[PDB]
Image 1 (cartoon, rainbow, N blue to C red):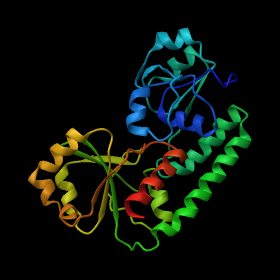
Image 2: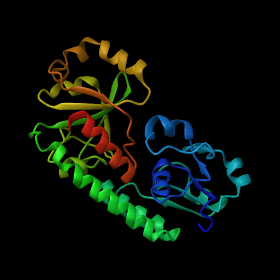
Image 3: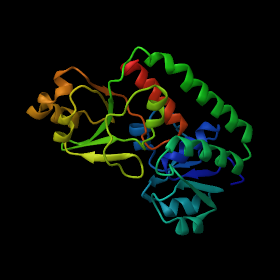
Image 4: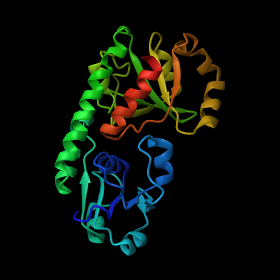
Length: 262
């Protein structure tokens, strides 16, 4: 993807890969929601919004003449169709088990394509150092499991399991993941609110994403008020963190994690 200033990112994972390498995306799919769900790595105003990740403005892309386009494997438009617009590459979020391991590989891969090998190494070094440096902030904490969630709608809570982006972080800090149930490839699964009642002695973090109306509707139900971890005072709403990102999202998680239970 020769011209580093004409790269269009059709999904948020590669946006994060580009940003970690110092690249300013020429175009980004759904800049609006990127701000509501990813937030942390801010996108400059100059970035062109090329439409929803699942339905990018194909005419716009064609007119833009991107030097290269990057997206997430198995997500969004057909890579075959996309490759017809401009050169491109899809990136894997995970191998289905360790998203973070893949993130490191993805960054490296992106760096090689753009000959930013050094920048990748500098970032990866900052990543591992940051993660390790924060370990002491969770030493005092015991073996109480942690439940990571986000409200999809009043009737559905998304929970992140063992193969979620967050697991590796939890593992390094000795924090058991309360959710050991099924998960999709991306490390999450949507469950009915009642399913959360099964958890008594656990801490629960819920990622906000400008959905106060929904959180309010949820918290007004007697069920939510009856929730053992709620009554136990173990529930906390926290800032949005992209669950399907890479190293920047992981580091963002650690910051949020720290403020919440560090």
